Length: 326
Ligand SMILES: CCC[NH2+]Cc1ccc(-c2ccccc2)c(Cl)c1
Image (tube, rainbow, N blue to C red; front, side):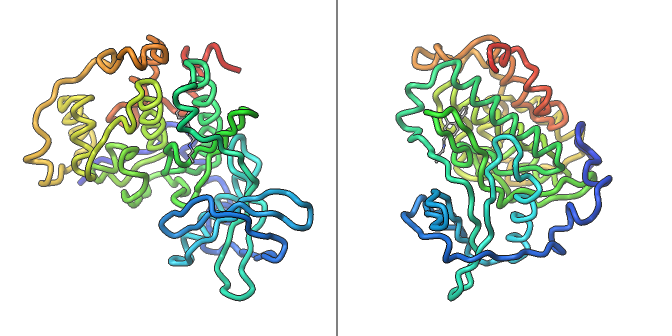
């Protein structure tokens, strides 16, 4: 069968804590009064969630209300428990209240408001420095949640809110987040296609916090090379092929040999043979002002097939790419 794996950092944080911390199924959720909140406007729509800008009428303060289509109670409980556990962590979205509609009884999560700047105007004005600055703010959030025994599992630009004027960053949407337990086999149907780590695409279930480090490398590559998304797969199988077109098929076979992974037969006719590409080949006139040897060394240490060989969030924060920050 497949070779077992465990995280290189924060491996046993949940093992040494009481069940109350990680047993989200047994957590008691207490709903506030939705009458304290007046919905202003629709901010977005997810699979089972509608996000609104709201007013807390009791203090005239702006909040964000995430109304969830209750399709799975267990999932809702998991998200609430994780949000409560992480509350007050650096750059983590703050859950302020948990409420139900007196009538429809739909669950709704109330969060601190984030004045997210339009990224379409932001992407062109961001400098080498701004990318280093915001990448470090995301690392703060990830080192924190991993130290708390949680993996986000949905790291992507749509889950990162930036108030550029106040240089404020928040990692949101903890709906796919999970407690890390060493040796546990997780569902690979997590993260958004372009940000899915090779472990997920080869169906290697014993993954850890390092999944988030792959996803972060994908956002970093798209930002520094101005190529969105960086790995543009059309399905989950093709997504591995797009990765192999960059990292090469040689290191891919080394990774699946190391963990005795059985490669799905659907990869037989699409994978082909690809050489390992130098990161310098993605440098062009449109992006050379954001690229540096430090950035390429940093990216090379995140985008690795072997989830164990990737930098942890703490090792990443210590990289020379961040010397000019904070
Ligand atoms: C509602 C869409 C929110 N998205 C905002 C956003 C999120 C992340 C980034 C970012 C990605 C990589 C490195 C540095 C920053 C940016 Cl530029 C913009």
